Image (cartoon, coloured by chain):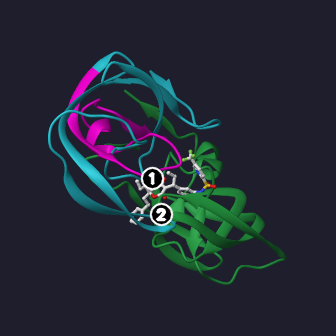
Chain colours: A cyan, B green
Amino acid sequence: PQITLWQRPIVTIKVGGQLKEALLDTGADDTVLEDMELPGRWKPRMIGGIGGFVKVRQYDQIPIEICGHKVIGTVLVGPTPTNIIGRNLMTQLGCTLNF
Amino acid sequence: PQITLWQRPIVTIKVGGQLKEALLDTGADDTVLEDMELPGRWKPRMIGGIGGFVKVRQYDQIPIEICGHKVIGTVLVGPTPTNIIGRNLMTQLGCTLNF
Ligand SMILES: CCC[C@@]1(CCc2ccccc2)CC(O)=C([C@H](CC)c2cccc(NS(=O)(=O)c3ccc(C(F)(F)F)cn3)c2)C(=O)O1
């Protein structure tokens, strides 16, 4: 699709069988999700946002459907104002910024 | 332009007579710049993101030139770790996400 920015660019994602809303965020290097159960082992990571740093759990090679497109990549789980889709997964979508 | 997302989408801006680099962030409601002087009255605000909340000064109707295009909007200033251009200005550039 083509998504304008007059409202938050929120899309429906499917992760671990669950439908969720997530924000397409070109300012985010990584994908950060609200607390949920994910399979496999996790590794520690610290990420920086406008408010400072947060400790997150890093899970690798997690499949997510974003608007019906299947992507598979790293997801970080921790305290966040909302589910955030970052550039790591937007590049798998072939997503670009256009003006 | 069409900007891919393999790297951070960073652009040159001119604001309050200062030239700076800033990150195009589709996930940010608002534009938030590192602490600086801007003309006019301001109001204090607390804005939330990853890492928590940041105290900012809100300036209204500030002209910013982004990649040569003049836009006008509210500009927040405070101790953000990076200059961020939010949706409030990206819309004025006609910027869309496409996949
Ligand atoms: C995953 C980290 C993401 C990011 C990284 C910033 C960065 C980049 C390079 C180097 C250092 C730091 C980008 C980002 O959009 C935000 C948040 C939204 C998730 C953000 C950015 C700008 C302003 C705000 N405050 S706000 O009032 O405009 C706002 C509040 C909430 C949301 C919501 F959609 F996320 F809920 C969006 N905007 C928040 C952030 O806090 O850090």
Mark 1 vs ligand 1: CB below 8 Å:
no
How far from the left and from the top, in percent, is residue B16? 66, 77
* Label 2 to label 1: alpha-carbon separation: 8 Å
Residue at image coords 60%, 69%: B54
Residue type marked 2: Gly
> Would residue B47 appear left or right of B81 to someone viewing this image?
right
The foreground one among A21 and A89 is: A21
How far from the left and from the top, in percent, is residue B40? 82, 77
Is residue A74 one of those drawn in magenta?
yes
**Does residue B21 sit above or below A58 in this rendering?**
below
Is residue A50 one of those drawn in magenta?
no
Tell me if I can see residue B51 in this picture. yes
- Which mark is drawn over residue B51? 2
**Mark 1 neighbour density, 10 Å: few (under 14) some (14–19) many (20 or more):** some
Mark 2 vs ligand 1: CB below 8 Å:
yes
Residue type marked 1: Pro
* Range covered by the magenta-colored residues: A70-99
Residue at image coords 77%, 79%: B39
Residue at image coords 65%, 37%: A6
